[PDB]
Amino acid sequence: AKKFKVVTTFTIIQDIAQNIAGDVAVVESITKPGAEIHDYQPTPRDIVKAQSADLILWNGMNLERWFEKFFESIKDVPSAVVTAGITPLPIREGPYSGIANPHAWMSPSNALIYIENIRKALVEHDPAHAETYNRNAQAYAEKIKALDAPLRERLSRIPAEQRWLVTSEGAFSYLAKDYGFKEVYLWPINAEQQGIPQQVRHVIDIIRENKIPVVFSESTISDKPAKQVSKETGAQYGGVLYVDSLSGEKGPVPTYISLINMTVDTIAKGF
Ligand SMILES: [Fe+3]
Image 1: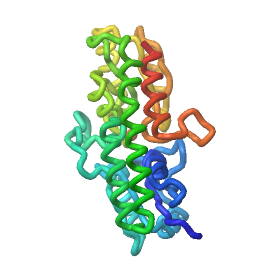
Image 2: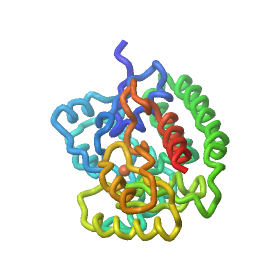
Image 3: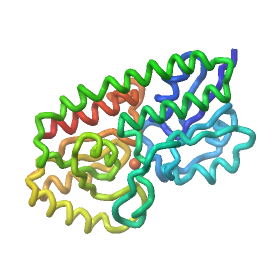
Image 4: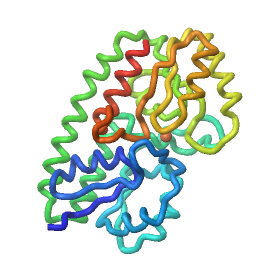
């Protein structure tokens, strides 16, 4: 029959929700793999897609600067914020200083809270399949819990004072806290903004003082600033990390678990 339909704002939530839904519901993302999610510009096709859903999931913590305006065009579709109950880390500098850092899913322990909020919403709005959602959610939570040991072991060759995570967007604060990294970034959160040219200068100073070997970019933004930082410092360009989007289904990062694993693997490789 016509399955229960879930529409999410972006792809990370889509993949977590589809694991809870199983074959009982269809989960689709508004944004496409690779697309920039903070300042995404919704289209009329997106309105129809969201309006066709039985349930809409979004991150909150003002990740989707577009969502609240967009949702005003949607009628009679329930929504749920999937970061309910997560304690935010605040943005530390720049024009969004003090706002929640929205990238909470980069902590796998936070992902357990994402999972519970999505399970609750699915059970509430599709009670006919509650037993499947509950079974799937507990099974998926166990797979997330099983990542912690291999993740920490993968990063264990890097001594503490050397654990510096230099990226483009400061999107990794929750992962960095979880695994004991100090964070440096070229801009605090994706946005149209000033201060990136002069922040590139400051990051160049921090790398030299701390002999940081590697700097990274991310899959939905330009690698040019991080590549420039590598050329003006003694640091390697360690490649592309994944945070704001999955890849395509055939790509290297088709799932949330693969995103966490590949990002940690890529960091580890860089040292
Ligand atoms: Fe981001």
